[PDB]
Amino acid sequence: SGLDSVLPPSLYALVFTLGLPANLLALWAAWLQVRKGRELGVYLLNLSLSDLLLICALPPWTDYYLRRDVWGYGPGACRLFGFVFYTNLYVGAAFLSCVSADRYLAVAHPLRFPGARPIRSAAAVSALIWMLELAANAPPLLGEAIHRDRYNHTFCYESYPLSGRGAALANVGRVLAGFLLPWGVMMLCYAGLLRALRGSASCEQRERRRVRRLALGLPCVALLCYGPYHALLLLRSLVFLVGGCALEERLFPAYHASLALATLNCLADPALYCLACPGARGEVAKVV
Image: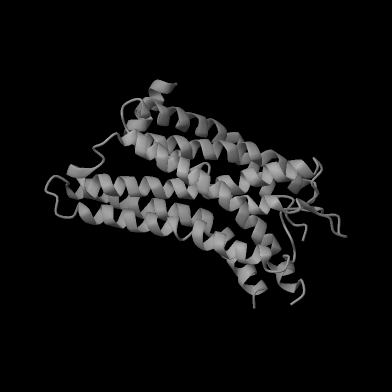
């Protein structure tokens, strides 16, 4: 423990230096197309909102890491900032899944979707998702924020080892129902999208490769970002449910490296979902 002094702050600083303008421009692009009756715009709006809140959560965590694990700001700040961070993390994946499902429906069933006040249903689903995520991430706020230990740490929302299966089954549920359910929906919906346009006489060979690249890539980018953290969480938890602090002492730097890589997906989502799209980039040019 204690070789987290370089990497997490580096990634957090890069995020706060580029994503915040990127997230702001993506948010403006998303709003500019909700005005034009679109219902992917609300999903993108909520996604960019979640990314912005995560970015605002970042700097206290940067100080928490650089100051060698202590939470100087006090117990309440631990609850607020940890709650914001760990809830926006899953809200992003849920809204990525919603975007994937919406695109899949609009492509596979063109003459029947959406057709009936598209914006309201999408806003209702967005509100329902936010309610579910907050209701799932409230119990960790129900417990003690800070755990002081001997070795100059004073943890916030972390325990090494964990505390008696109460956090452990919560962690396994959080893994299997905040990742690998929405990522599974992502992969299946994008595969269905790339399968439903096989048989279309309009699409050429060239236009089909673009969709193939996008459909295979966005699940892959999301997995490469949110995978190390959740694999490590599932590993620690499934071990806790089966050897001192040997395991944790081994995989601790890997754990926080994984968390930094996971929060790195606040530059990828704005890029891929705003600048890659020709229409959104066009409004972005009008945005500037």
